[PDB]
Amino acid sequence: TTTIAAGPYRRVGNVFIVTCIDHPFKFSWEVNRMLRELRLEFMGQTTVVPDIPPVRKRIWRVRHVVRVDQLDLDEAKALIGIPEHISFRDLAGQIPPTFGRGGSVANPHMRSKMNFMRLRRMRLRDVMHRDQLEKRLLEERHHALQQQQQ
Amino acid sequence: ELLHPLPVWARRQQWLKRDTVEMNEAILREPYYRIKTFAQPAAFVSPRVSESAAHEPDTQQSSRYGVDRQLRGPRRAVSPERLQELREQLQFVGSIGPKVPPAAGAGTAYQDEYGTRLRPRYPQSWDTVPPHQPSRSEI
Amino acid sequence: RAQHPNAGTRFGRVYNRGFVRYGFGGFGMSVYSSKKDRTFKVMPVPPPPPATTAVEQRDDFADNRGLSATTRTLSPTFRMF
Amino acid sequence: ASTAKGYMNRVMVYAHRRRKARYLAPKNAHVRSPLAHKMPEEYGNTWDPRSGVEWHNRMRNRNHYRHWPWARWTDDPVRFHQDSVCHRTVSALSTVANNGAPEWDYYAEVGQAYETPSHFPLSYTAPFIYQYTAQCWSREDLQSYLERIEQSSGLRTIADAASRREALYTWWHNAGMNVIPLGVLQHLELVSRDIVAQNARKSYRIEQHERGILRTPEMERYYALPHLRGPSMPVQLAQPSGKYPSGKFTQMMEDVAIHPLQKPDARYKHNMYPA
Amino acid sequence: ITRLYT
Amino acid sequence: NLNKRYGAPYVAKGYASLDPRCSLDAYSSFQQTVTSADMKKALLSIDSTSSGALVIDVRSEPERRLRPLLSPAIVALHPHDILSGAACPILPSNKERAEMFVVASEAQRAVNACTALRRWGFSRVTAVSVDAVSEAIA
Amino acid sequence: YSEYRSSYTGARSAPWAAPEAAPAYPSARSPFPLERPRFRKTHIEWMLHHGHGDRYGKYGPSREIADFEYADGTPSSISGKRFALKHHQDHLLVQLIRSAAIVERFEEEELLPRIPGTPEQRSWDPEIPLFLEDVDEFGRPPRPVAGATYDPAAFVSDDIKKDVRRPFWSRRRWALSDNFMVPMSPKPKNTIKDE
Amino acid sequence: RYRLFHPVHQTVPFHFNPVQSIFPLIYENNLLAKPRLSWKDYEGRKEFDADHPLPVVGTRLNERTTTHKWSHWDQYINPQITQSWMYLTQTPEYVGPRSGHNVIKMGWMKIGGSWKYSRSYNDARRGFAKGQWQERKMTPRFMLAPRVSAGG
Amino acid sequence: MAPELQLEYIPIIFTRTILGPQGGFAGEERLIKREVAQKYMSEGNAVTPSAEFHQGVWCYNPDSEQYDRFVERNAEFLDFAARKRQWLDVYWRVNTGYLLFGRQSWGQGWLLNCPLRKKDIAQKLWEQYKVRVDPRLIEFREKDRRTGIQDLGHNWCWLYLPGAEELAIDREVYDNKRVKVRMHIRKMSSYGALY
Amino acid sequence: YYRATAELDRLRGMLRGRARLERKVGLKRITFLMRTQTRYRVEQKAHWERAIVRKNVDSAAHEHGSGWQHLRNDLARQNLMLLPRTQQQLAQYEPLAFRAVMELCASRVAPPPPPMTAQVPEEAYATRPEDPKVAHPAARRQLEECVERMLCTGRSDVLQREGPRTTQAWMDAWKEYDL
RNA sequence: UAAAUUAAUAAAUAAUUAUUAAACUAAUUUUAUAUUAAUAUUAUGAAAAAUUUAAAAAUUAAUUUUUUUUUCUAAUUUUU
Ligand SMILES: [Mg+2]
């Protein structure tokens, strides 16, 4: 209406949807490195990366390999039916941090000892459970004994 | 070796290539954000400057009219004050921490009724698939 | 002879059809060129009927018209609901 | 496509080696090349090529460079990670005095973009001084110190507090000394000698950009044409065409069109009997 | 070869 | 054999569709003037019950603290949010009927920000007065 | 009975336009925004356009809908491959929600730069204008009153000129045209760095 | 043509997986998170109704097994089953006799495998040279160092 | 000053008007290489900036061939020796530079399969030499006005430096209004080649 | 190295002369003729075999004046999703039904719209004043849109009424378990 | 995969590979990462490029390649 709109100005980021259109095995070891940091190896793979600055370089180096698409965040809160009031830093604050392939630790061994202990803190979760039953029965067997003499 | 010419058909599908890259780097020089207002519509038309050869206008039989149906539509959270009017109603059911139970009318919590390890008996089927092995989400 | 794994094709070398063409680089071999492709290529399209509609029956890449313009014969019998 | 039994067993028709982890860097080791052991952005550094085996043994954490940066960050040879602000003070009331002393320049070596011109009041260098003195004075406390300086002393501007560091202190000694911790002052002196410095480096950077030095935001030179003050294509400065100017009309070679009534030069053919 | 599961 | 498949607006295209001419016209508007009435008309655009701030100030954040002009709710945009195109989602629809203004610390930035606007398809903006809009308090 | 969902919520947008009105056909020109080649959607851009993947049985109503069901109605069971699809679907949402739970963070701490394009990129492309603020891009401002315009089109002529034959049909114009460089015969691709 | 221009926004269609899938009560604002964490966590096939039991159509993980020999735990629990000396099987750590050629530089090869790459296994089976300097060139590190303390 | 550490280039006020890149013109102050400048202060084309020369200097006219022409450097000339330098710095930068390429070329005709755009020369001007221009000025040759550059090896194309008439700039550059930017298209495999 | 002899030893019974008699030449033949089938079959049979099916439907689309060049793209336009192996069954065994697909594509009928992504039911934008006994406006929104669709599928006994069945009481079928 | 110190010219060394085993140091996305130790080790020369020595008439330097298809099916690169 011929006027610079007036109101409390919120800023919305962008979210890039990246696909892979050229094979990775034709390119260098650095270009393959960027694709790896975009969770992209095979042709036809597809990921949803943010528009943060150090991603903008990774995507830039491999522009000749990927086919990007940009979404403003409001154009993402509707691509998946999302109420406008719910942000995303509370939606993620709900999913567990151990989603499929939890971490990316520095080598497939450190991966295999990050999944190991994760399969241990399950064992301990039942074992910290099985003694917490005993420690309460033991603290009662003490009071039944103690109060027995009175 | 390289004996006979690139079938001049093929180099055309390679002129589409540089005109793909010439369309990526048009995306990779967009501003990192967009100064937007609450009151105004979400994305009344408000696209990027991608009105070079604009298509799919038909508002149905158009791919985007699952989305811009809601963008162009009047934005409900019309002010930062209206946001807290809306953000103060949502709960977090599973998040770590303490809560205040009687904040509702008469609800009596669930996790303190069937314990923490037991999950409701979800009907497993093709269409309805519930989370499997729930004791692996405790990190 | 330096017999090291990773120094060439791991165990000997084989020429499968995905290699004799599409060699290292995609051109791809110097010998064993490839078999000629003796499949059955589809035939090119018949001519469309004359226009006599004035509805721009000529336009090929338009939203309204499906590519095929086949108004052949007892097609009016194929009345669809 | 041609997927065959497993992750990383895709196309399997091209003859590349799958299962080869192309993302991982080459083990250049002994080979001598600028491309050695360098993250690809550091390729232009051909003055410190990182070839050689010992660079393979120490970038990679090999035999006895097993903790290679034998002195990485997080050690200080000098002050051993203890803040140098004396708390053992004569009077407990005045222990809070020493808080906020500058351990180094804090302002020049960082190189912040102080967009404050040197003639602003002092109260507009508070947002900078704070970011190095929180845990010492609340932000709204500085605006009580960085105003009593403006009110009591004869100093008002960032340029003043850089030209009157002597006249300022002598005020503080004989008038302040009970409220304004001199920590602020030597902080106030360290910014006012920077905001004044940078404005000299900005005002110069704008004054060359007219004289035609033309460097980018990241300060790399970029060469670009000046603005036009006269006719674009030179007229009294034009170099001669450079090809022998036998015009199209002295030898009517081509590109010449003539009315048929006005046909020229047939003095022996059809101009002898002109019409 | 570390997987990604994309 | 391009320009047969693609048009002439191919290879003969100076893809620099950014600023071959607008920058000049930016220094044109710089020349003429802006004054009270040139704000008083904008005052009527503030008098218009529809409140979309007309003028905008591209000035450093320490500067505006010194001479605050934010009174009529005018827009304070960092000069890159204009240049980069991050401000188009708040900019009038009538590119040919709207004329906002641009205040700035020293008039070189103003024209250097208004040329960014005219690069974004905007037609009328006379592009500066750091002191008038304060003398026109409204 | 058969079923046709096409989405998690059902409620397909009405397929038929109106009792008799125009039918509103979809855009059938491929989104390749140059307008000169004028392509067509190619039966994979017309499978994507209908909400499959680039293949028939990926992401589409051909993969969500049950293989079968016990004729009484008792539904199928969770195929060991089906569950791994629901995890792949959720892994895209979470790939989107996380990748916006980071952005919704960055704008909070102003961490998003105002200058668009990484440092290395901006040196590479000359269409992102330099982000000088208080100077002019090309040195001094047009101090001279412009009314100062150069039009590329006047002097820069890119004309695809037909290389004209030396006209043999007329005698004199054959002799002038005899550009004495027909001794191009010294074009042997000779040894350019040895003798 | 194979250079398709489409909104790659199309290739991950969210028609079937909107946030009402992973967050099943979000239009209910309580925002509960019930995702499917991994393909690993899949508990298994389960009859939705008891009347339609899932068929027993075995796989290469059932129809191809072997009789359970008694492990040293099953004989530690119930010593009533160690009924013959064929039940006193060796230590569990003893997997069995050597069954492959640990050729150097190439893993552990099977017997009957390929000897294209055992060029130096056929040469590290003869044994180290006996009575011969280990260091063929480069002035053996022992000879370089000086004799000290005539006895040692 | 030491015999080891010598100023790699020194300040210089030109008296004559030298054509070369290190050259200048009448009365401008330029930091030209030391070895070159040192055979100017002997030659007389230049003199180190003593405080006296910073106001006027007796430059040279080829008319009478002696140092008679007094060119006084007031603030106005210092707005003239800037635009005249800033101009012929773009000249001597693109004319000296030899901007390289890496491209893909299958087939036999040594033909670059995705031929070059006037976009893709201003792009390799700003990339390598930081010369920021309008790609509307770059006129291609006749062989490459149709299909773009299109061929490997050495190509050149003309860049039109328009605004050189009020700078009085001729005979000190090879062509007042053009300059030959000199491509070269070093074909490369998918490893290092783009597009 | 194990030549799977006992897997080939009984299958030389269908080779020809010299191969059947001797073994080391019988195996060598079949363990090659087998070794090339399962290499021909994985990488070469389809892109031949799936060209007979294309050459069939084409020349069966060709009878009706359309080509495969036009039919292959005019099917995906109509979201019709018939794999070519099926169009070849229709080209032969159900000719009329095939030409029905033919006359459909050539028709100017509006192809079905792409599916709409999930929408936000507008009750998420109201804040229910939480009373224990009244349902949230977004549940009784979802429910009615899930019960109207359960009455949609299959002729059943569920409150069997002509056409659309009974709903406003189906949503409140919990009170029928209430005391 | 490697390609360096040395050889009256290759049983020896690096580097690689291998067997066995390891610990989660700022840098970022909520991204992504095979880094090591201990031993075993009869090896001197890298397609197509990009260039560089050389009468080379190839050798040499160079540095990225360097293929193991469960079965039915689907497909976007066409001896026009
Ligand atoms: Mg097959």
Image (tube, coloured by chain):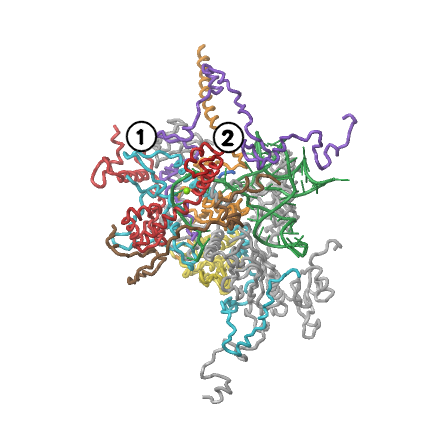
Q: Is residue A96 in sight in this rendering?
A: yes
Q: Colour of chain G?
A: cyan
Q: Nearer the viewer, residue I155 or I160?
A: I155
| Dot 2 and dot 1 residues touching (CB under 8 Å) | no
> What's the colour of chain F in the image?
yellow
- Judging from the image, what secondary structure is the residue with disc 1 in? loop
Residue at the top extreme of this rendering: A149
Q: Which chain is green?
A: K
Q: Colour of chain H?
A: purple
Q: CA distance from mark 2 to mark 1?
A: 38 Å
Q: Along the horizontal axis of the image, is G51 left or right of D162?
A: left
Q: Chain of mark 2?
A: A
Rendered image quadrant of residue D80: top right
The red-tinted chain is J
Chain ID for orange: A
Amino acid residing under circle 2? Phe
Q: Nearer the viewer, residue D126 or C81?
A: C81
Question: Which of the labelled discs sits on residue A116, or is there none?
Answer: 2
Residue D69 x/y as whole percent: 64, 38
Label 2 environment density (alpha carbons within 10 Å; few <14, some 14–19, many ≥20): few
Residue G115: x %, y % from top left: 52, 51
- Name the tint of chain C in the rendering: brown
Residue F129 higher or lower than B90, as above or below: below
In what quadrant does ligand 1 lie? Answer: top left
Q: Are both tags, 2 and 1, on one chain?
A: no
